[PDB]
Amino acid sequence: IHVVPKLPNSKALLQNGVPNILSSSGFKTVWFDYQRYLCDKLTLATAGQSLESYYPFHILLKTAGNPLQSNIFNLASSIHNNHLFVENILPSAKTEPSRLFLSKIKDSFNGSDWEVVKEEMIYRAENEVLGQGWLFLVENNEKKLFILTSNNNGTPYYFPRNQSFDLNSAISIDEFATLKQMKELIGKSTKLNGKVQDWTMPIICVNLWDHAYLHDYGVGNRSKYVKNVLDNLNWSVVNNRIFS
Amino acid sequence: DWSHMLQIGRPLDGESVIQRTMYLIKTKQYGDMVEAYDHARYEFYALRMQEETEQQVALEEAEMFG
Amino acid sequence: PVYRLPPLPRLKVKKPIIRQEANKCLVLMSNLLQCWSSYGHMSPKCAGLVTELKSCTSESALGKSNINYHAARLYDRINGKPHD
Amino acid sequence: TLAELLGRSRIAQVANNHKPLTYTGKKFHPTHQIIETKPSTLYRQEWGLKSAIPSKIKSRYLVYNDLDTLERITTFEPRGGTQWNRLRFQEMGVPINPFFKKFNTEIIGTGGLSYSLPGKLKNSPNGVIQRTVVPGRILNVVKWLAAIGGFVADVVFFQSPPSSFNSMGDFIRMKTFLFEILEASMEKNGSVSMHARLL
Amino acid sequence: TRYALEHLKEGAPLKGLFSIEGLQKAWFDRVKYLDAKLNDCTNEAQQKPLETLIHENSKSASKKHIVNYASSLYNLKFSMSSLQGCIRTPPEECPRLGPEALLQTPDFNRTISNEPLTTGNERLQAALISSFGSLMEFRTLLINSNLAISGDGFTWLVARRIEYDKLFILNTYNAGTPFNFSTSGVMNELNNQYTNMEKQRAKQAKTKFIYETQQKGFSGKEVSYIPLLAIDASPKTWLTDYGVFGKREYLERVWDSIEWKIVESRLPQRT
Amino acid sequence: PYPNLIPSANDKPYSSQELFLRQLNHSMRTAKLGATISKVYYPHKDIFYPPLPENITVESLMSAGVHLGQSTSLWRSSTQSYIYGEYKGIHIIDLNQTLSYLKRAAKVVEGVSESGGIILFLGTRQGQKRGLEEAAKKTHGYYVSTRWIPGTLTNSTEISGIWEKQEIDSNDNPTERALSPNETSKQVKPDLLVVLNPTENRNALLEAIKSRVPTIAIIDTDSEPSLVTYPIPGNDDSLRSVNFLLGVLARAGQRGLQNRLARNNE
Amino acid sequence: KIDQSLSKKLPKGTIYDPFDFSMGRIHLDRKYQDIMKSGANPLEFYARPRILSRYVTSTGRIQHRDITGLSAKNQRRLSKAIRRCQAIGLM
Ligand SMILES: [Mg+2]
């Protein structure tokens, strides 16, 4: 039985929700209703199996390579990502960005400062993520940050399941080349499961699903919601997520 | 509560069908064993069809999104 | 039908039979001899086989049953004797 | 009471089955329930059965007949193959209605193999999947039969067999081919008769 | 403009399916935003119809947004066009379904409502029985397919190729196209072009046989589909009113809200 | 924290050990996000978080598989009174009798530990070492899991006389006093012996009988109840049931030890 | 070519596992390689030399119950019927 995690200051979040991003009704939709929905669906899908004993992150890491249980993976991914998202918008466990994170953004993004990087992430979310999706700021094994976007329920950890390219429409030839090299990397591995190593981790997570913003911000104006999320993050969690 | 087949913390299996059959007979919603067994069987078929469709559609979506 | 043996002092095979695999050199020699029997000695047809033999025996001319142990180990468990 | 709980216990949930574990006859459908144990319980040889399974077993699936016997052994087999066949059928996508509206023992429609409905097609990034292709192995030099994804089917040819067949002879099963599943039907006894075409 | 439909009005509801706010947000705000983006990306979309835009602007990464927004608007219009409403109680008045909805079992294998033939749509129901076994099976398959869509998407009824040989049910995701000739062969095209590049600067042959096979057909290599009906799985339509747990309630009310005369009008004759 | 580790330069990528520490930091903080697992059985907890004797229900004993007895073909008819019935070719143990006997044996273990007696946990099946060791450590007792040397009690001088002994206070604190050779060569006899597999340890049971050592054991359907002072009807061939009962007894012993220390610290 | 005994033939419509395409499967199959078992009276088959001849060797020796696999009752009736057939001039 997967159960919705308890959140600090739950009474205040019920009363008002996350300040300056969501109202109480919106926070109910994004977390109290959607997280319960996802957890119940995962429990129904994985009950009576081994996967009931593993956490959603270990579930999605286990299930990433098997086509026929993608649904479980999707649920697991959401159940993880949503919580990550919530944790970077919780009022508290004003928090300030750390020196190390600022240095990494400055070094990772070709000298660009953090705020223009925020605007660039807003642009990326507006452009590529058509409809439901997730936005992440992630660090790779080279100690380099970069911006990743996943369509529907995708994971930053495993690059085969990043779901960063929307094939329903066309794809740029460069995106096709990226897909082909990715598939070659997958195929090179000698493991029977076909697994590959990916040490990417999410430092920032933003929920672009309609549950997050539609009730508070409408069909349009999603970039407004993303800007509000990024401006008022809980920087203690974000700083802790980085390793030194 | 066995008014419905799906239980949280339980898989969806044939034993759920037998449990729903016994619940139906106990409440006397149906009289004969065969009738309740058939009704639970049809609920089982509906639920399993829904799960099969979720799996197929999920795999198709995954391939759709790269 | 099932036959149940009495409580026996032991459970052992007198002569365990092992599947030694016939040496490759011997069978290759036999094939060569049959070749020269049918086509003739130093016949063009099967001369290739000769090459194989020349290699197969070049280094050397010719190039285990645990049933009793396991039976003795397991007999007390599987004999199905009455309690005491 | 204890009797009620024993009636609702998972060991009781497994139906009484006593068929030979090692069966050399024709196999059309599963005959034993597959018992699964988590890796943590496998580490301690706990399978939910009466007694601990020997530590030699490394697989997480088995099929069993007796919880205990006179020989003090659990009558089991470390095999969980059949599920894969079922799952492999789901990869084929070929659909096969009794599932829509005194006790009868006939196999009801597809007995859990596939609960899909015929009228759907697969979208792919290349486009609509018109015809489903899966790899298989032609078995014998005979119609010709093929082992395709856990099931034996009779392959419908297209003009002549490729010359590779005649060259290889009885070593034909060594080489993989690509087939398209024309149709899948279920016979009364539970056999799944599929017709495929060698491309 | 052609985007807006006459059976929808600002400040007026669609009985049973949407409230005033639900219809507002789902349709009028969505079309406003979508047409704004579409006209911003290209001013020429005003002159040309959506289908012509989709056909002409496909297969180009630079012109992607044009096809994306054209398909979104066209599919939204196609989905809402078949709607008529239903006698069931207003969604606003009914208390929202909660977690219990997940545990309730569907009745889509033991019930049938809003059958086309009762209204007089005999040919449509005959064809659905012909290709999908029965309307019980058709309704189950359609609603299960649209339920399974995680995010933004549509479930389509389609007919093959004006006359059809056979009917089918399709899914499209984040502004996909129901017809197939716009996108068919794109991956094979890019694969061949990429191999030509890579050699200019065999797994490809084995994969190409399968590529051609997946879309190869009998009597022709190119396959087309007539849209006939569309449902919307996007949270935009149903999250506002029914809530997180109320997608199944939305889909059943949608099914009761289908008028099959409009669907028959789209039916392309017969082989 | 992690001495003798040489971090990498910012220009260069992470090292394998740096990646390991990074993933450990991720695991201890964020890997467990999304849901909290409830009502799921984790085997290790049966050793580390055993329930108290009073909190045990029949449902908990049945979940551990304690009720599953031997095959009906291997029945020892002297165990008739402990049997609830037979089902699927095996005898079912009456779990209410099991609960009563287990509570009594737990009280015995708690009393013996509270008196400062020596408690010996003997179990020689394959995977029983972990639970035996943990029970002995938390009861300040002793255990054997490799093999019971015959004559360990009746011939203690020739078996256990060479190993070293130790004087300790009321609080189990080493005194480090020098023991005389005669004191070192005396027999030290267990005050309580608990056997997980009494069928394969007849020698230990007979030695305890001869040496007047009260003994507890898990009495399966094919085991003799009268060979032990405090039988516990239950399944002895499943590691889960054995570990559950052993953890209950070990927690009772730990409670007795804690009571003893609390009284000595007042 | 492969001798037929060395090859395993999967029948049509039967499921299989990868183990089936193995010599172990052939060896296992080798290892585990009518009317009178249907509740009939063998004494009634005393003027029917063919069906009686099904249960004798080439020389006419009655086959043991280990070979026939019949019940003791039907085995005795079969022996009696075969001997009666021998006596009356048939068989
Ligand atoms: Mg035992």
Image (cartoon, coloured by chain):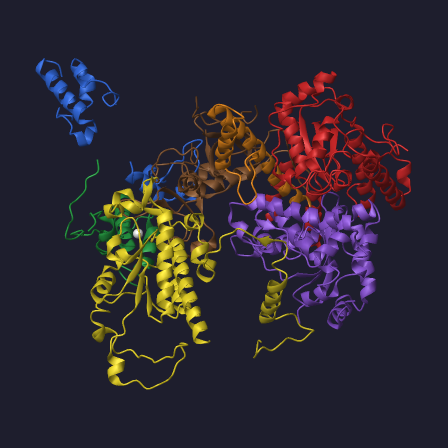
Chain colours: A purple, B orange, C green, D brown, E red, F yellow, G blue
Q: Residue E239's spot in the image, x, y percent?
A: 75, 41
Q: Quadrant of residue A199?
A: bottom right
Q: Is residue F156 above or below residue E36?
A: below
Residue found at the far front of this picture = F266
Residue located 29% across and 60% down the image: C63
Q: How many callouts does the rendering have?
A: 0
Question: Image quadrant of residue D191?
Answer: top left
In this view, F206 is above or below D95: below
Query: Hey, which residue is sitting farthest left in the picture?
Result: G87
Q: Say left or right for E135 vs A225.
A: left
**x, y percent for residue G45:** 18, 15
Residue E206 in the image: above or below residue E230: below
Q: Is residue F27 visible?
A: yes
- If the image is split into quadrants, where does the N terminus of chain D sit? top left
Quadrant in the picture for residue E271: top right
Depicted B29 relative to depicted B56: above or below:
above
In the rendering, at what x and y percent does residue F155 appear? 20, 71
Q: Nearer the viewer, residue D80 or E42?
A: D80
**Residue F99 shown left or right of residue A179 in the figure:** left
Image quarter where the C terminus of chain D lies is top right
Instruction: Confirm whether residue E225 shows in the render.
Output: no
Front residue of F7/F165: it is F165
> Viewer-proximal residue, F266 or D184?
F266
